[PDB]
Image (spheres, helix red, strand yellow):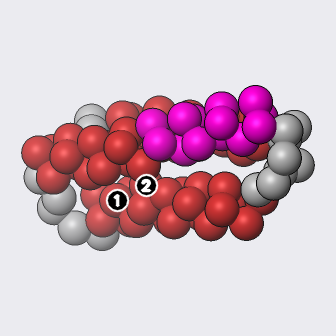
Amino acid sequence: QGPGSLVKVGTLKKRLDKFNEVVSALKDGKPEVNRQIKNLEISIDALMAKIKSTMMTREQIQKEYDALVKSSEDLLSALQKKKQQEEE
C-alpha cells in the first residue's frame, strides 16, 4: 500500500507553508490571511485523514484540489493588492 493520491495533497500543504512565509513578511491583514490560510490548512489536512481513515476517490481529491486552487489563487491576488496597497 502507498500514498498515491495523498502525494498531491501533501504538495499543496507545502504551497500553504509558502504562503505563510510571504504573509509573515507582510504583517498586514493577518486576520484575513490566517483565517483563510487556516480553513485551507484544515481542508487539506481533512482529506489526508479521509484518505487513510476512508476510501476517498481520487476524483474527489482532484476537485477538492481545485477548491484549494480557487481559494489559494484568490489569496495570492489578495496579498498582492495588500502589499502594493501598503495600508490596512
On screen, 7 above or below 27?
above
In percent of width and height, residue 53 lies at 30, 69
* Left or right for 60, reference 21: left
Q: Is residue 88 left or right of residue 34?
A: right
Residue 39, placed above or below residue 26: below
Percent from the top left, x then y, of residue 49? 38, 65
Q: Quadrant of residue 70?
A: top left
Looking at the rendered structure, the secondary structure element under dot 1 is: helix
The question of residue 81 being in magenta is answered with: yes
Vertical comparison of 84 with 2: above or below: above
Q: Is residue 77 left or right of residue 82?
A: left
Residue at (42% x, 49% y) in the render: 71
Residue 8: quarter of image: top left
For the C terminus, the image quarter is: bottom right
CA–CA distance between discs 1 and 2? 5 Å
Residue 52 percent location from the top left of the image: 32, 61
Residue drawn at point x = 65 percent, y = 32 percent: 80
Q: Is residue 78 magenta?
A: yes
Task: Give, as a three-letter code, the residue at label 1.
Answer: Leu
- Stretch of the chain drawn in magenta: 73-85
Q: Is residue 23 visible from the viewing direction of this image?
A: yes
CB within 8 Å, label 1 to label 2 = yes
Q: Which residue is mark 2?
A: 44
> Viewer-proximal residue, 50 or 84?
84
Crowd around label 2: few <14 · some 14–19 · many ≥20 (10 Å): many
Drawn side of residue 7 relative to residue 86, left or right: left
For label 2, the SS is helix
Secondary structure mostly seen in magenta is helix
Res. 47 mark: 1
Residue 24 shows up from this direction:
no
Q: Nearer the viewer, residue 53 or 10?
A: 10
Residue 51, position in %: x, y?
29, 58
